[PDB]
Image (cartoon, rainbow, N blue to C red; front, side):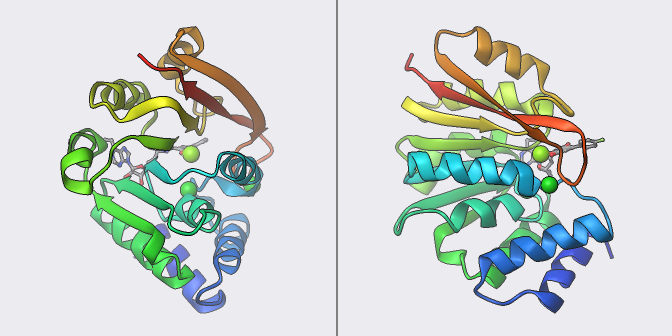
Length: 213
Ligand SMILES: CCc1ncnc2c1ncn2[C@@H]1O[C@H](/C=C/CNC(=O)c2cc(-c3ccc(F)cc3)cc(O)c2O)[C@@H](O)[C@H]1O
Ligand SMILES: [Cl-]
Ligand SMILES: [Cl-]
Ligand SMILES: [Mg+2]
């Protein structure tokens, strides 16, 4: 099997069904003690919690679910009736994420879309009944952050005030995206310095709030 499957099974073996904190803690312990994995992690995760609580979004889009760590983190903090859409191209990872959300008891808050973001984004309005997004969490391949930010705009999915929150803007880094939003009158940017998951290495999140066209 794969590292991702081993993470899920360690959650199953250890955590408590219906308890999202137990799931987060299980994943973090596995990935600290056994095998590193690219989950956002607890350090950055605490910043994400603070941002999600500040804005109280009704509709969040995540790009790159992976094993569902960040989807559990965000969905647990959504107000009742608010929703998360998460896109994941890898079918195996998409199924791991769904099972992780199911185990956490958060399945009714989250829709896992198995496909490439560039294919799914244009479908959001007609197929998933989206008007505009309140928040977008970027955590997929780093060279797709800028392409997909521009595609979101083109598709009319950003409103005045939509909060973009980008992982890994220091390591591995997303240089075209970061330079773009920081240089653009269409974004208001704030940097939250933190640490790479499971490591004593500086990373950070970028918050980039869309100002309108
Ligand atoms: C095609 C568009 C598209 N559409 C839909 N789903 C997509 C997608 N592109 C990618 N996916 C999925 O997203 C996830 C990949 C995410 C990529 N993430 C990092 O590379 C990364 C690396 C480090 C790090 C590595 C090594 C180091 F030394 C240090 C840091 C730390 C981090 O937090 C990181 O996020 C997987 O589930 C993909 O299947
Ligand atoms: Cl994650
Ligand atoms: Cl961490
Ligand atoms: Mg990341």
